[PDB]
Length: 304
Image (cartoon, rainbow, N blue to C red; front, side):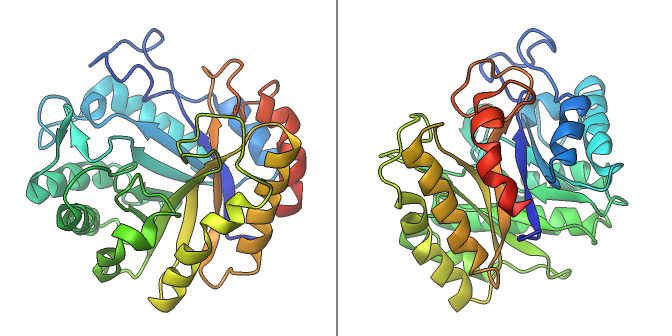
């Protein structure tokens, strides 16, 4: 393997985010361990599992978990880690809980102690503080990431990596513009990884199959790479994608080839996304018929 980690998001448990609690099998679904196994057989060793904070811990983030949703999170994590791969536990929440900005680091720390306690003995779990903080106070984003770390380590979950995320939708291309204060995060286990996301369409939203140019990915990560190096930090690309076309194929490999020459800071990359409810989605990595599984995975083989 070229990178420490290379794999895919396994999306579904966060679907239908407007329906809370929502109903499993109707509004959301958990990943399929059999198709995860296929991706593992292809060489992937990390799987990021989005879920909603409100579905895992309803009403108040300081309360008790929902038994049903937690049981399925547990089963998904174990399906990944029992094979030897890493499972990223991702509260896919944008820094918000019931659609309000999480303004209490203390409440967030308690949420994270609750979650980390369920996984504290599993060294292949990775805790991801929150997906894509955005449009909120920059000091608060720093403090929420630190509160998550403190809660996780307080639970005795000390072996695991922690993926921290920044503002501006944790974008790599925007990182130095807004997220410099993230350099001050502390972890007694010294296992912080800075998770950045990078899409390749014009606005970086990852909603169009069209990429700006054949070099846009490598261009959009250069300053983030320099920031990680200058500050003595390590990073991962926790979401990236491009359409099944020639320009995007080239942009994807150019980005990954650049990361491969900068592994002093880059630990790897995670595609967005696999999962069982993507259908004809332009970026679907879901075996055996997702568009990216068929048409993009062949160009990712060099990194597996």
